[PDB]
Each structure stands twice: as C-alpha cells, then as structure tokens.
Amino acid sequence: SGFRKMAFPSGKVEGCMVQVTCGTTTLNGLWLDDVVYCPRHVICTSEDMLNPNYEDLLIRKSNHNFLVQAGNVQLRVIGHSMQNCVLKLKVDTANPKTPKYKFVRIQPGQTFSVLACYNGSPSGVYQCAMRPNFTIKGSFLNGSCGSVGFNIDYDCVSFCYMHHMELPTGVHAGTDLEGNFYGPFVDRQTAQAAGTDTTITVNVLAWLYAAVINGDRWFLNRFTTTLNDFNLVAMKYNYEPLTQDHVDILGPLSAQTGIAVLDMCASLKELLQNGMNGRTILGSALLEDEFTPFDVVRQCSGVTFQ
Amino acid sequence: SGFRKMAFPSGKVEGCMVQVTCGTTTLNGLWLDDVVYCPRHVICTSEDMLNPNYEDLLIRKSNHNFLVQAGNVQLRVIGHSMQNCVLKLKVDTANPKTPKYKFVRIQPGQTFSVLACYNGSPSGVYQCAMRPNFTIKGSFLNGSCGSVGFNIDYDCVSFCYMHHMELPTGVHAGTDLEGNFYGPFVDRQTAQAAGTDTTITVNVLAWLYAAVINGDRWFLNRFTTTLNDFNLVAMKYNYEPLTQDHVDILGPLSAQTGIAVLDMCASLKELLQNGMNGRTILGSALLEDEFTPFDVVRQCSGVTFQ
Ligand SMILES: *C(=N)[C@H](C[C@@H]1CCNC1=O)NC(=O)[C@@H]1[C@@H]2[C@H](CN1C(=O)[C@@H](NC(=O)C(F)(F)F)C(C)(C)C)C2(C)C
Ligand SMILES: *C(=N)[C@H](C[C@@H]1CCNC1=O)NC(=O)[C@@H]1[C@@H]2[C@H](CN1C(=O)[C@@H](NC(=O)C(F)(F)F)C(C)(C)C)C2(C)C
C-alpha cells in the first residue's frame, strides 16, 4: 500500500552526465557513445543572448574551444555540429557506460523523471509531467541546463527532454534530444510567455483509481454520466476533454476496482461542482494530475526494470 | 526556481541490491563488500510468522539453504549470522561496486530517499520523512522487504533504513542497518499499531521559507510572537513544540529572506487558526512537513554530490 510521487532509478543516466565548458559558460552534457549532446547556447556570451546568430557563433569556434570533463577525465573534442537547438560534440572516447537508449518525443500529459545536474554532477531526481501548454513545473537553478528527462522501458532508457530555460512564471521549457523545442519557445532572452494551462483529466481519473485501490472511497457515488455530459462540465473548469481512447486506457484500473470509467467521471463531476470540503484524497487537498494511468498500474502492481 | 519532492540519485545504491531466496521466500538484500544484509524473516515460512523463534529457525539452516543472486551471477554463501533483526550473509565475492558508506540511525523529522526494489531489481525512488511515531508513509508491495533508505553526504552513502513490514493503517516500519527497529515494533505477525502522529513544525517552517524564496508571500504578516506563545498554539493543533535549536537551524533561511524565525511563526500561527481558505502554497492546499531545513537549502541553493 501507499502512493508516492515516484521517479525512475537514475543509475543508468548518472553515468552519462558530463560537464561542458565553452568560454566562461559551463553547463551539462549527455555523453552517449562518442557524442556529447548539450544546449547550443553554451556558445553564447552575455552580448549574444538577446539576439544570437548561432550559425555565426558556431563557425567562429574550433574543437579546442570546448572543454568536456567526465569527472576528472578530460574528453578530447574531435568534431562538432549543430542539430536544431542542440550541439553534438564528437569526442575521441566512446562512453563505456552507454546504456541501451533511444530518443523519443513525448506528448502533453505524459510523465518522466528529471535528473537535475550542476557541473556534470547529479544533484537530485524527481518526477514531472509535460503540461498541456508544453512547459514543465520543474525545480532548476543556474547551471542546470543540459539536465535530461527520461523514462525506462525494461532495459531501455528513453530520453525525452533536455533543459534549456526558465520562463518568467517560474516554469521550465526545453527540447527533445533532436533539439526541437517543446512548445512555441526559442533559445534567446526575448519576452516569451507560456499559454494558459489546463488540468489533465485522464490523469486525475487514474489518481482517483489509485485512491480507491488504497482505501479512500468517500468520494464515490452511484451515479453514471456520459462522455458528452462530463466533457460539458469539464470545459467549464478548464479540464481537458475526455476521449474514448482515454476510457480504454483506464480499462485495467476499472477492471481491478470494479468501478466503471463513466461511474468515476460522475464522482469527478461532483468533486468539481461541490469541492472537497476539507477532506483529502491520498493526502492531498487538491486533485492531482501528474500521474498517468501507467504510473498508477506500475506503482500499484510493482513493475521493475533490468 | 521551483520546488519539488526531490530524491537523491540512486546509482550508487542500485549497484548493491541483490535477491535473497531461502525456501519459498524471496526478498531483497544489500551487498556491501563480502556481506549481504537482509531482513531475518527471510528464514520464515507461513507457520512461523505468528510466533517465530529466530534462534531455532536459524540453527536449522545451512549456508546452502540461502540463494543469493546479483542479476544473473549467483553468490556463494560461506557463512551466516544474525544481528538483531537483520541477517548478515557472508559471501565469497566482495562487491566491486561498494561505495564509501556508513550506517546511521536517523531521528524523527529527518528525511531520506527510498530505493524500492523487487527481486533484487530497483523499481523506483522517492523521498520520505521518519514520522514522530517512528513509521514512514512509504509505497511498498509484497516482495519489497530489504529495500533500503539512504542519504548522500558528498561522496558517502549513509544507509539509515531497511524495510520490514506494513502496518494495518497502511504505513511502514523497519530497522536501521544494525537491525534495531525504529519504534516499538517487532518482526512478527501480531497486532501492532502505530501511535498517534504529529506534524513536524520545524519542517513546516522550512517549507514556508521555500515558498517565500519562490515568490509565494500572501500568508506573511507584520506580527511577531514568542516561542512560548507559539508552542501553546501548536500543541492545540498536534504540532511538535518548537525549540531554540530549531530556531538556530532555520538561521540560513531567515538570513536569505530577511524574515525572522519568530515572524514566520506568527504567519504559521495565523494559518493554523484561520486555515488557508482555498489558497495554495507551492501548489499545495495543506501545510507540508516532509522537507527539512537542509532539504530546502539544498534545493534552493544547488548542492551536488561526487
Ligand atoms: C541554463 N543554464 C539556464 C537555466 C535557468 C536559470 C534559472 N533556472 C533555469 O531553469 N538557462 C538560461 O539561463 C536561459 C538561457 C538564456 C536565458 N535563459 C533563461 O532561462 C532566462 N529566461 C528567459 O530568457 C525567458 F523568459 F525567455 F525564458 C532567465 C531570465 C535567466 C530565467 C537562454 C539562452 C535561453
Ligand atoms: C516484505 N516482503 C513485506 C512487505 C509488506 C507487504 C505489503 N507491503 C509491505 O510493506 N513484509 C511482510 O510481509 C511482513 C512480514 C510478516 C508480516 N508482514 C507484514 O507486513 C504484515 N503486517 C503485519 O503483520 C503488521 F501489521 F503487524 F505489521 C501484512 C499483514 C502482510 C501487511 C513479517 C515477518 C513482519
């Protein structure tokens, strides 16, 4: 029993983190085989961040302008190139700790673990979701750029996020590992704002199932609603609309608790209209939307990795 | 910016987890140098759990009754002994991944990371606090026994917790690594209950400072109270009393925000008497007590590890 915001074990990623210095700017890089990936703005100074021309900045650099350290060992850079918003640094030594990996682009509502790093050294691990407005609510200080987000599928690490910047509302924006931004952001110091965020409905439902599995039942009722009646209520409260695909995804949780998806929507419908009235669910007084259906199954059934 | 429930990177611990089988019972063990530590009830069957006599059960075993696997490699057990509630299995191979480590007993209110494991394989990592009633609010399924809790101090892993059991309220109890239980619990299937829990006041204050650092200021006020006036209010709400040592510990956070500890107590005093009234603090509608002052400093200043 119990329910916690659980991250993936980070061992396989810790062995890939390196420190990248170019000029007076130091940040983190990801070392897989003989390539080090890092944010391209490592080649920027202060004069450059308002309106950088990265093609110009890069041609004016040579391999020896880039200092790559894996702990104390220095890595010799033998070639560099730019792919969208990431720099790919070819080095003379392949990382012997390279795990089986792939590069995936995730969708809003999906979750991943973040290994926050400073100077190539891992500082902490935490779980978060990609918000519907393509930002993440992370915890990041100066120097954290190049920290990566990831999932683990059996033995395979899927990298899905590299950190680039903090927006003025205190939320965080970055790229996939091919260097393409999530959301309409750019890596310069211009005036950028996230769009309005919405609550991830399928995730709230998954969390209500986790609560039932763990013995919190007080919000249930006998009513049933329809997909269209629910979605009409959800839009009023800035909740994402629910689709038949979401219903099917919630199947395993419905079967395990004997509570039909559309039954649970009627409970959620009541919670949105009447509030929780000083009661808590799994130790929270707000509705939690950063657990996917698969997170709940994994934590309430006990899937491991190798 | 931002604030997350952050765990320590788990790499150094992942390399020490093994699977221990005795009979039809399999659980996790901790492999440091040539010793494997695991819960002693691995030597129990179903008939034994109501009233086990562990001295009798252990003398009736030999080294070959214990199957230890580190992934696929089998470890040969060359000797065994009991230390309080843990079994120490001497093996013929010293773990080459043994980190610099020590065994520490933590106090109520302190936090640590948990590497949850099944069959020797790491499943997830999460942060929790040792509650004033010596339980932890973990997330654990069947087979998770022998999972460990730990902190990292620079390069040194301090192991502080090994998991043994779930209580009927759904909370979790275990031992330090010398096998001594936290709290008045025993490793048998008798009727045991945790005592009443209290809120960890020094931790709530640290979290309020984190909120100020991150721009949440709405709960502040101009009032100041005394230690005795505050503690008189805290006891009414089942909060731990505040000591001068706690005040001193909150020093760095007071200096960074320019808000005196006793000023912040007056805000907390108001929040306890009037509630939060539909407002949130760092994304929570309840007062959070599982961040120590040191957790806040670490996350809002950016201490790494090597
Ligand atoms: C990478 N090392 C940092 C990470 C930041 C620092 C505070 N927390 C974080 O997540 N990234 C940057 O310094 C990037 C960098 C220039 C500007 N920048 C920012 O994060 C700034 N934000 C923006 O300009 C905005 F609002 F547009 F996103 C800052 C004002 C420092 C928060 C570049 C090249 C994008
Ligand atoms: C170790 N593999 C498990 C971990 C448990 C299973 C569910 N979640 C957990 O944390 N530990 C046990 O099976 C221990 C084991 C006998 C009884 N036991 C329990 O956890 C049981 N609880 C108690 O007997 C109680 F209430 F006294 F704590 C159970 C009913 C299965 C929850 C021994 C030797 C203590």
Image (cartoon, coloured by chain):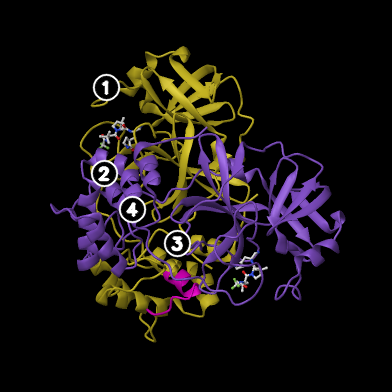
Chain colours: A purple, B yellow
**Residue occupying the point 38% across, 25% down:** B42
Membership of B209 in magenta stretch: yes
Specify the quarter for ligand 1: bottom right
* Residue matched to label 2: A213
Out of B74 and A282, give the one closest to the viewer: A282
Residue B46 numbered mark, or none: 1
Which contiguous range is marked in magenta?
A: B208-219
The three-letter code of the residue at mark 3 reads: Pro
Label 4: how many residues lie within 10 Å, few (<14), some (14-19) or many (20+)?
some
Q: CA distance from mark 1 to mark 2?
A: 26 Å
The verdict on a common chain for dots 1 and 3 is: no
Amino acid type of the residue that numbered disc 4 sits on in the rendered structure: Thr
Q: Which residue is mark 3?
A: A132
Camera-near label (1 vs 3) is 3
Q: SS of the residue at dot 1?
A: loop
Indicate yes or no: mark 4 CB to ligand 1 under 8 Å: no
Q: Residue at x 80, y 45 (%)?
A: A91
